[PDB]
Length: 99
Length: 49
Length: 50
Image 1 (cartoon, rainbow over the protein chains, first blue to last red):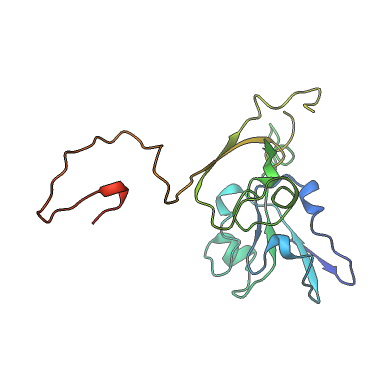
Image 2: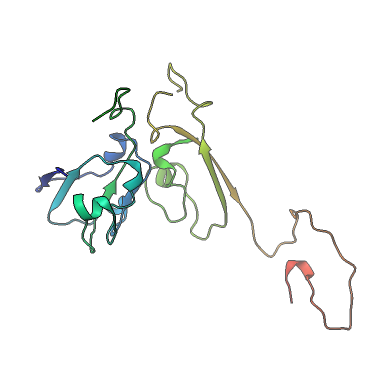
C-alpha cells in the first residue's frame, strides 16, 4: 500500500547484472524479451518495490482481479517491461511473527 | 550441471550466456528436456568448485 | 547449500531424437503382427500409417 517509485533516466543500462543480484526463478517480461534489452532502447525507466505473499503473486499482471489488484496495486492493460519476483522467507520471516 | 538462473536458457532460439558460449540448441530441435534440483549432491559448505 | 533457490545447482539432462528417413534402431515395447495383402486395411508399415 506504500510502494516506492524510483525515476531512472539518462543511464547506460546493462541488464545482465540483475541475475547476479537476486536469486529469482524467472525474469518475467511481458512485452519485450529479457535477453534482447541491450540492443533496443527506450525513453523513461521506472522501478517499483513491494513485498507481497505467495498467494497473490499471479495478480501482478495486466487485466487481473484480486485484493491487491483492486485495493493495493493495479497494472495497466498495455503494460510493457519486466516483473521480477522471488521468495524472501529467509529475510522477511520471524519466529515470533513478522508484523 | 547449471545454476538456477540459466534453466530457461536451454531452449531452441534462446540467447544468453549458456545458450551463446556454453551450450547452443538448434532451432528445429525435437526431444525432451529434463531438469531437477541437486542441492543435496552438488553443493558443499566449503565451496563446490 | 546456504544459497537461495535461484542460485541452487540444477542437473539438466537433454535427450535428442534423430527423426530422419534412416531405418529405425530404437523402438519400444510394441509387438509385431503378421502381414496381410490384396485387401484394403490399415497398415503400420515402417511406422508410417495409412
